[PDB]
Amino acid sequence: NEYVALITARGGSLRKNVLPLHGIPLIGWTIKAAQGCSYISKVFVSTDDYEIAKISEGLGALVINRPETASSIDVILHAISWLEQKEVQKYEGMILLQPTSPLRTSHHIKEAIELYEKTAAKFVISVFEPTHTPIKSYLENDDGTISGLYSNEAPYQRRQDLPRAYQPNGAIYAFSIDEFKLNNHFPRNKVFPYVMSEVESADIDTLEDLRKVEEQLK
Amino acid sequence: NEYVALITARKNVLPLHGIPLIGWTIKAAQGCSYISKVFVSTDDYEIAKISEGLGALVINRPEASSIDVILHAISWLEQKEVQKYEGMILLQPTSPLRTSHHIKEAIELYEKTAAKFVISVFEPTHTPIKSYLENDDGTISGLYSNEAPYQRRQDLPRAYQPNGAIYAFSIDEFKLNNHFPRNKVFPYVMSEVESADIDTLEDLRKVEEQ
Ligand SMILES: [Ca+2]
Ligand SMILES: [Ca+2]
Figure 1 (cartoon, rainbow over the protein chains, first blue to last red):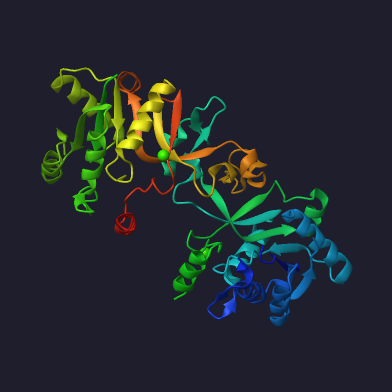
Figure 2 (tube, rainbow over the protein chains, first blue to last red):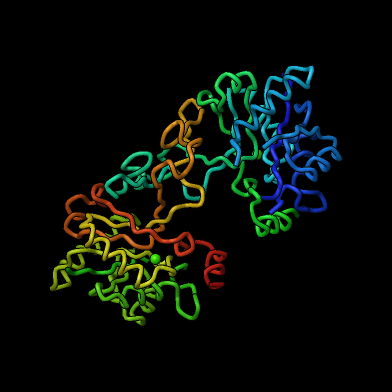
């Protein structure tokens, strides 16, 4: 089994992917995390921006030049098409890695591929259990009323007595290139969770997010 | 017509801008024109001394369940109070950012909608409507629908989380069920900022800095 790492990074309009973090641009961490994992064969950055592509090429990553608020699937399908045409080796699985998740390491990627193999999953998605579990939330009805999202008794039943609810952190998406091509979407069946902490689930959007992560890092 | 405020009680006495945490919820209830009397359901002499100091009336409870504290309070009110109260306004002492205005707007909605229950909520930054539920085989699928984690927020129905600041219900309905109404429940929506529930000392520190 051969895996390819795909890192999707666009340009500014906040140019977050190139923001410095402990002396390496944000995207650098995710390229290095991918490159440092023994299961990853090649690392590709789909970018529409010169600075992202030059940084990427500087760290030994291969640039997928992307054309012109585009769909995320249309980016993966383009990447799959580019890989089919420009690469000799057939890749089994794609490891989609968001450049704004610097706290997701090579170990996380390793453990997520190990689970994708062990469970023989169609899809592995990196998740976290929120502090306020969605399993005890309420859903707004058409009349304006509210009732339990899981069941009517759920907001009142304790956490232990209810099934685990997860939120995606967007750090890792491990899937089969062949299945994705068939559907033109992510697998809706045999989807398994790779559970990470709420701490490790940091998604840099603002400079306060970046500052918290600069501090966190020690 | 008539509403009674019930505040169920080391966190509750923690100082916040010169008043113990419970003081804020006591004052918020007392400052609302729709609230007739304010009680603090507590099993500690130090909390009951502070509560009485801030003009709240103490319901002395025996030295854990939330419903057992609501029904005890209802029983105490039946026996020790002459006036019959229609609705109970349950107010958590760990929600100091919930004001008399919030309580007012909450009761105004309980009346306007003619609800059986009104619960103070907030729309989380990560909507529960786009979350995943763990199956028995170990697999995961959308909590609302299988397509939900992939459908955009706008195209999906509003999911709320309770902040626990306000629970407006009928004393007569809760007595017969021995639980909260499961029908005609309406949401009173507050911000994620106003939804602060003091648990840790970092939570208090963040609330002081406001
Ligand atoms: Ca781990
Ligand atoms: Ca308001």
